[PDB]
Amino acid sequence: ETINRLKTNYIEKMVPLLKEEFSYSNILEVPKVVKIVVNCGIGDASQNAKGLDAAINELALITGQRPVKTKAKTSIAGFKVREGMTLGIAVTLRGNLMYSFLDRLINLALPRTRDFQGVNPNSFDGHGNYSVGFREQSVFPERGMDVCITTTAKTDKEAYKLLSLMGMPFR
RNA sequence: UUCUGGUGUCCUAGGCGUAGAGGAACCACACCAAUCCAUCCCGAACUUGGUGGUUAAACUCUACUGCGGUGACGAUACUGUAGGGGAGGUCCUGCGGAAAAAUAGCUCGACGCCAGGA
Ligand SMILES: [Mg+2]
Ligand SMILES: [Mg+2]
């Protein structure tokens, strides 16, 4: 019912709770979410403009922020592309948007996925960061995407402990 | 004369890593706000204006020779010069010069200026 749940629930309840878990000598050693990078790659984006200009608006309503036409780092003929042409669709979420986006993730989009049985807890990279893959975006109440969550954690255990508190149903 | 910060020159370039110290002041980060300004998206960075929590990260100081960097003397190779062998490939001698490599060893910088503090 409150305005910002995660921002208030984190600073008040989680930081005293997560500090007691690992017994950090300082409060600043606690991890926290830095950003959420939402990628959406389309190889055939160079062909059409309607499918490009439309999908850019689809993600914007999901995030409340414009995507960015991500360009190629180098040309290659195996996938018939050229340098400087747009291939990916990306955006950066920081501050309150990443929390508001996470509220729309665990409670709106992630439950509505067909045949849902929890997300893989082995998706951590080994340095506290976490990633998610989608096939559809209509689960958001308004094609796939690679949501990349960043965190200041060194190991994955405190991250798994961190993410699990803010929902994130793991099998 | 020392401590902190700022700013340099010299230099064998003085770093990585490990183990400690620092918060009064100083430096830094963290927290909040956003139309002077900014984002091929995002107040992260950049810019204003605020709260002072923390030395966690950075940075500063103290130590070492584990990596790294540095590095001989001596000897030998090579070589100038005057000569001499061998069918040739190439080799030897006298006078003079003289390494690289490796090892020992050295190395966790040296010296200034301004402000503040003692
Ligand atoms: Mg010698
Ligand atoms: Mg040598």
Image: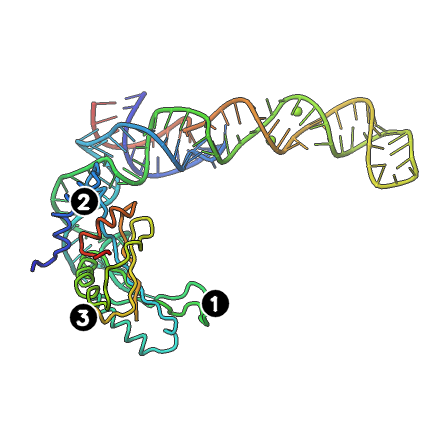
Secondary structure beneath label 3: loop
Image mark for residue A141: 3
Return the x and y of residue A15 as percentages of the image width and height: 16, 45
Direction from residue A43 to residue A130 in the image, left or right: left
Is the same chain shared between marks 1 and 3?
yes
Ligand 2 positioned in quadrant:
top right
- In three-dimensional space, the C-alpha distance between marks 1 and 3, rounded to whole angstroms, equals 38 Å
Q: Provide the residue designation for mark 2.
A: A18
Work out which quarter of the rendered image holds the C terminus of chain A and state it: bottom left
State if disc 1 and disc 2 touch (CB < 8 Å): no
State if disc 3 and disc 2 touch (CB < 8 Å): no
Which numbered disc, 1 or 3, marks the residue closer to the eye? 3
Q: Is residue B106 placed above or below B91 in the rendered structure?
A: above
Q: Is residue B18 placed above or below A61 in the rendered structure?
A: above
Q: Quadrant of residue A138?
A: bottom left
Return the x and y of residue A28 as percentages of the image width and height: 21, 42
